[PDB]
Image 1 (tube, helix red, strand yellow):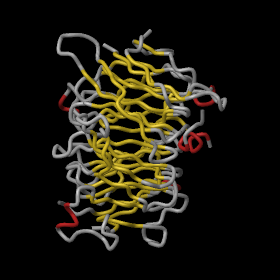
Image 2: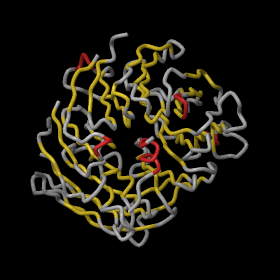
Image 3: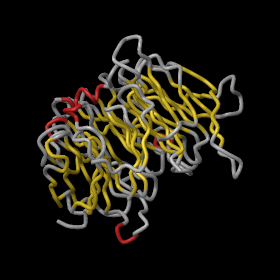
Image 4: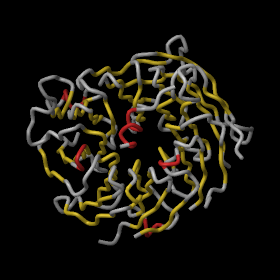
Length: 394
Length: 12
């Protein structure tokens, strides 16, 4: 069964990365591998989903493209990050009722050897700021200023606190704090713009408001941390890790106490998401289940969706920000998995809304490795291990 | 080209 309304098969191998323009959800960039041979480079494309033909091509990566992001608030830049450690920065123009979006390569840098993720800063005060986490554990924050393309990239921060690979990062809603986690079990929440330090709310390293490591027995998740999310008020951060473990840690408002410890699921928590408007946290696990916790009730278990993606890993969960059906605002969760399926859930109960097939399953060389769904969730664009990009409608 | 760490986590 194939439920897609459009597709893109331009990638020669697995597609690992996807990003979406924050103003124009039809503009999507995808990135991945051109093959498993050493002489096979990475490759990215930009698509307009409004068989798809790309409107731009991202070359220059000698290894797989692993991370992509458009900048906030307006998508003035598109940035790619590779397993070669290259960060390539493109300026983005979207004509009013001129024509197709246009892209211009501005700059390339190589601050790390391998980029694991990007996250754009949501602070309205600091437009075109992005963070990345790398295999060397470092976390970098960059600001992009198109004026002076002799140096359009400026370094806001370069943190070297994690030792092992930095697996995930999440900004607080006000964009002043950046929470990152590592394979070495540490959590650091950086005071990116110095505000916390000015209010005497940073730790002894002068850089974080929270720093927790393997030596902290109440916190340590044996086997590593792989996911992180920050609550919509910025009051807490959730970290997810090996063994199905989740830790909830307090943040200063603009701290570092364990507010709850969760272990309903049985294997790696690969994805965490707070609902933007309902008092719930969703967690996706390598064991194929999703668990939903009530954030106003000491993270009491609301529901355990076993076999949400059979016994195949749940790769990503994400709430629909503002669905057209406003009654469901905050309660609609989209998930994707190595079963090759995308699903959407109604989390009001204590619930499958839709499922979209088309990708091969993991055992056939497929699985869904990522997706975007815009603000409304009405179009879902996927990237697959089977080298295909699919478009579904809600 | 290589596969990211997370893919190796998913695979078993």
